[PDB]
Image (cartoon, rainbow over all chains, first blue to last red; front, top):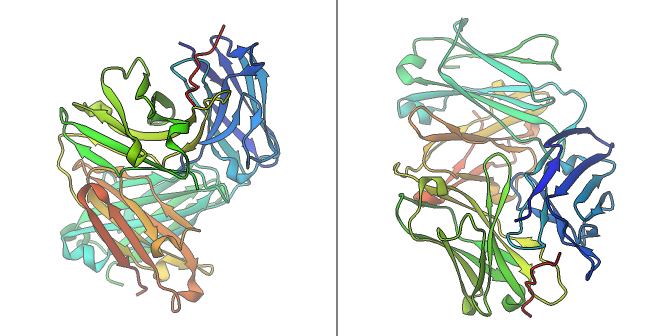
Length: 219
Length: 223
Length: 9
């Protein structure tokens, strides 16, 4: 049983710079008969199946950018990505196929570092459709920001809310390298009607002050 | 056009049987093995094994040996992954891929299926409610309008959302699902568009929840 | 030292 260990586990690299992932085998996967290394590299983007980049350790797959290069021999292999582009954001895997089982390395997450971008903030009162079913979800959207650290606080009639909201963050975008975040305040219809002003307050390092987006119920 | 297409997401109770499929086309089935690969939460891939259709030769990963079975239908150029009795911990995304069986070829995985999410759970299947997130002055500024669909109270994953039948993809954010207190999932999909063209363009979110056999097409209009 | 041959042709 041959195992692969990748280093580092995680990686944040600026656009246009070089990324380097190492892969080390517990046993050599070099065959002198072949003069080949039984190793492959894969790219796994969010929402996509894994994609083969290199086989025989260093043979570039047809259609794979010249910016990618695979090197190494025996137990020691390297994937290099020059001039990092936005679309390179992904998990990267090495795999051996020297004997069975054909194990993968544990994976390396590549994050793209871009310039600081403040979130654009949008808010949505509950739909009339939802309210008819007895519940009110208020959605606050923080769009296209970098870096990932962003906080949302809900205020209802200027009272800080706690324990009635959920949030979710996207994966990093393949085109503009940003994140987006949704925060949803969920109340009963009866509770939603006790109050007038619903406010989402957003903090991010690309902002100099907390940004508030609010509406009055029924407007 | 090389293609491996797997069956849709499936939901079973623990102890029940399940067989998922990998329909291959655009190449000679007998010139390749079919591999099955499990995607681990967070990070990681598990090579589960390979099967050759020409003689039913199978190589299983030792850690799945005895728990799963592989089979093929060469007439249908299809490979199958079998569980005779599922565990809740069998829940996950499973990929199929092809592996060259010709002499002097390497055994890298050069073409992959889209992945299928198997869920094993005692919880009840539940279709989602879909509500519009209409563009308003409160979701419009700087020339950009945000709009979306709130997809609430479903089980299990996955829900898929496309816009205008896949014709609208740029600026689309379908957020990772959240687990609600009820044990049900919820997500929203949003898109930003020019505020200047809300009068000329139409925006429809196509919501699919295969485990409940549910399809919703919600037109999202300003007001 | 030697790989497991998976060739079938």
